Amino acid sequence: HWGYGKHNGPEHWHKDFPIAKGERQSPVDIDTHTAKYDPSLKPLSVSYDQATSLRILNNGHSFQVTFDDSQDKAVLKGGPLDGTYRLLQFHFHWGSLDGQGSEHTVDKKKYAAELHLVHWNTKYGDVGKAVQQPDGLAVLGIFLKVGSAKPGLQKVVDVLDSIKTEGKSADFTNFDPRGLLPESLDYWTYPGSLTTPPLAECVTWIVLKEPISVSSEQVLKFRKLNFNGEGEPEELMVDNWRPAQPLKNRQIKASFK
Ligand SMILES: C[C@@]12CCC[C@H]1[C@@H]1CC=C3C[C@@H](OS(N)(=O)=O)CC[C@]3(C)[C@H]1CC2
Ligand SMILES: [Zn+2]
Image 1 (spheres, rainbow, N blue to C red):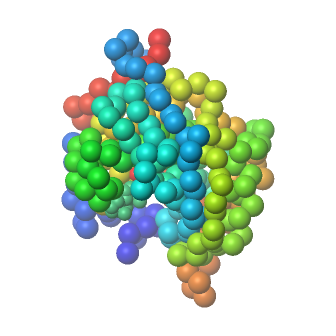
Image 2 (cartoon, rainbow, N blue to C red):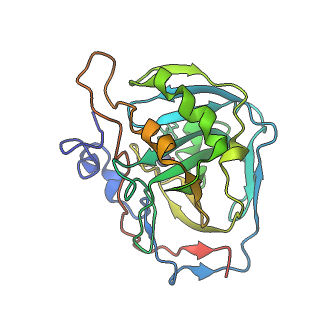
């Protein structure tokens, strides 16, 4: 029922998911001058060498690449985190045009897209239990700007024609998510939420300062995806981003000066 349209979009979500108006909702605007450098924050540890991608899926709100999370093969640790978080999936948010698409903003700047790598805390055993905990999930967010192509993204772009409509999936083995990361792991962090229903307040957000560049041809392929199923009136999967929510009583911390 929920989506990104006039009648079912973000301004409507609170009716089915009242936590939409909660105290720690995501995304937020990152005010770079107000974020506090925290010299106590550790470097982020990203261990993706043994990642096992399984499937690529059009879920009617995004596309996602799913990983084997039945063992500690692709894990996030350190940074603001206590313990070990397993990579479950990555997905994107993007715009109809390059001047919007990101969920987080930086001094009100919107990027063309935002990559989310979703991880869950192994101490809760499964992602369904982790989403019920305030420290259940860690989402690594990476901004996309349009310029030079990202070679590590092309394997993803080239299969999107095979998952055009909602629920369509394909084999997507041997994909290396290290090819989507920028040089720097400098980050901002704050306590927040899932940015789609059920909007659970279970996420430690880690948003990298350095964007990756993708080409216009790569993001154009995102914009050919459809929100609709098969045989239903064609609606381009574009503008699948929630806007910035109130920061309320939260501090954004920077890992860098
Ligand atoms: C399947 C599930 C119930 C148990 C685990 C839940 C997952 C956990 C994480 C996310 C990531 C979120 O996107 S975002 N933008 O916040 O990273 C979209 C929603 C989704 C897929 C939940 C949907 C409902
Ligand atoms: Zn997301």
